[PDB]
Figure (tube, rainbow, N blue to C red):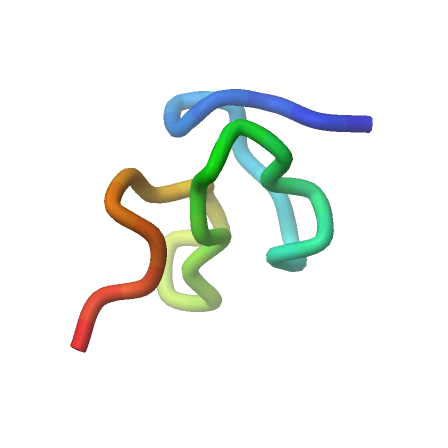
Length: 35
């Protein structure tokens, strides 16, 4: 159960391609989390 940045998820556990699932838009993000 892994998708890309444009994939879309509800939790970070979904991101397996070195992405971070933001709780804002509920979608994976590149460069991991954003500060």
